[PDB]
Image (cartoon, rainbow, N blue to C red):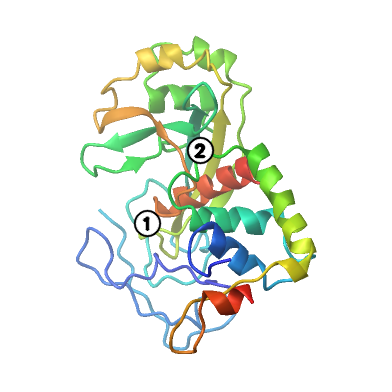
């Protein structure tokens, strides 16, 4: 995952806390915060679907990696893939 | 715990007057502690020991722009409904004064022992109260108690009771009231069911009321 975007910033902020900590209020707060426009068009049931998808993504931590491209610290896309 | 003293009642200059309130620090606000040189001037607009302010010391003595000493009460009913048919947003029949140009509430001065039907007829301009007769059993009890205000003194203060009546999707008692919705009270030149929100950037007493309405509504999902 890229460390700059809108849904990529959601998982880049969720991937610090443990799995128990995340709730439906936190993801609703982050969706209001990152999708500034078009947040309104979302159904609560669709929010209930994402808020299960995101914990099933966070369940296996050895397939999920956030990187951040910066040439000063000698870090690029190949480093993240490797 | 936080913001314990009242802060709109200790403005150094009294509103619409030349008199100045006494200076009162934040430590000596409450009635428990004693201020040794405490001597506020007494200047009633146009039995001053009958009551005590529930908030605290204020540095102004008398009856400041009020018909009575003690509490002056104002009821604030909010006639709310849905905005669209698909229930995507909410709305409230708020007023917007021609002098202030701000979306204010429609709530008037509730007298001591005032009937709610005739007071709502005065505050709404009821040429048709049969809709409010069928909607008389609607919702209420949003908030109740003390209101910080510039007008508060040591003797007189302002208390309010917030009530919110949110109708159904159709709101059958709203068609006659919207047909009777014109420039009746002569202060609010527009008056319609503008879209409600969770606005804490509103009128001071009304912002917590809208936040409480949103905390009621949206918390379930």
Under tag 1, what secondary structure?
Answer: loop
Inter-mark Cα distance, 2 to 1: 53 Å
Query: Dividing the picture into quarters, in which one does residue B100 lie?
Result: top left
The percent coordinates of residue A66 (x first, y second) are 61, 71
Residue A60, placed above or below residue B168? below
Residue B57, placed above or below residue B16? below
- In this picture, residue B8 sits left or right of residue A69: left
The subunit letter for the residue under badge 1 reads B
Residue name at image x 43 percent, y 85 percent: A71
How many labels were placed on the picture? 2
The percent coordinates of residue B187 (x first, y second) are 25, 33
Residue name at image x 53 percent, y 74 percent: A77
Can you identify the residue that label 1 sits on?
B63
The subunit letter for the residue under badge 2 reads A
**Label 1: few (<14), some (14–19) or many (≥20) C-alpha neighbours in 10 Å:** many
Residue name at image x 76 percent, y 70 percent: A62
Query: Dividing the picture into quarters, in which one does residue A12 lie?
Result: bottom right
Residue B216 visible at all: yes
- In this picture, residue B114 sits left or right of residue A25: left
Q: Are marks 2 and 1 on the same chain?
A: no
Can you identify the residue that label 2 sits on?
A41
- In this picture, residue B10 sits left or right of residue B110: left
Of B216 and B33, which appears nearest the observer? B216
Image quarter of the N terminus of chain B: bottom right
Q: Are marks 2 and 1 in contact (CB under 8 Å)?
A: no
Of B76 and B203, which appears nearest the observer? B203
The percent coordinates of residue A24 (x first, y second) are 69, 53
**Label 2: few (<14), some (14–19) or many (≥20) C-alpha neighbours in 10 Å:** few
Under tag 2, what secondary structure?
Answer: loop
Residue name at image x 48 percent, y 77 percent: A69
């Amino acid at each position: 995952l890229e460390g700059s975007g809108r849904l990529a910033d959601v998982i880049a902020h969720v991937a610090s806390v443990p799995v128990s900590k995340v709730t439906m209020a936190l993801i609703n707060r982050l969706l209001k915060r990152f999708f500034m426009q078009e947040y309104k068009n979302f159904t609560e049931l669709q929010i209930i679907e994402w808020t299960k998808k995101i914990q099933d993504i966070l369940r296996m931590p050895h397939l999920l990696t956030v990187f951040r491209i910066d040439e000063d610290k000698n870090y690029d896309v190949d480093v993240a893939i490797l | 715990d936080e913001e314990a003293p009242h802060m709109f009642a200790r403005q150094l200059q009294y509103p619409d007057s030349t008199v100045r309130r006494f200076p009162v620090p934040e430590e000596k606000v409450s009635w428990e502690v004693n201020f040794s040189p405490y001597q506020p001037p007494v200047y009633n607009q146009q039995a001053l020991d009958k009551h005590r302010n529930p908030g605290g010391r204020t540095g102004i003595r008398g009856k400041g722009a009020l018909n009575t000493l003690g509490p002056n009460h104002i009821l604030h009913p909010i006639f709310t409904r849905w905005r669209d048919a698909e229930h995507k947003v909410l709305e409230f029949l708020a007023v917007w004064e021609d002098a202030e140009k701000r979306w204010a509430l429609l709530g008037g001065p509730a007298q001591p022992d005032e009937p709610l039907a005739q007071v709502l007829e005065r505050i709404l301009g009821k040429k048709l109260n049969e809709k409010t007769k069928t909607l008389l059993k609607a919702g209420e009890e949003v908030y109740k108690g003390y209101v910080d205000d510039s007008r508060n003194t040591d003797n007189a203060w302002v208390e309010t009771s917030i009530i919110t009546l949110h109708c159904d999707k159709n709101t059958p008692l709203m068609a006659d009231l919207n047909h009777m919705v014109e420039s009746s009270l002569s202060s609010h030149q527009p008056l319609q069911w503008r879209e409600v929100s969770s606005d804490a950037c509103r009128c001071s007493y009304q912002r917590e009321a809208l936040r409480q309405i949103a905390h009621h509504h949206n918390t379930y999902f």
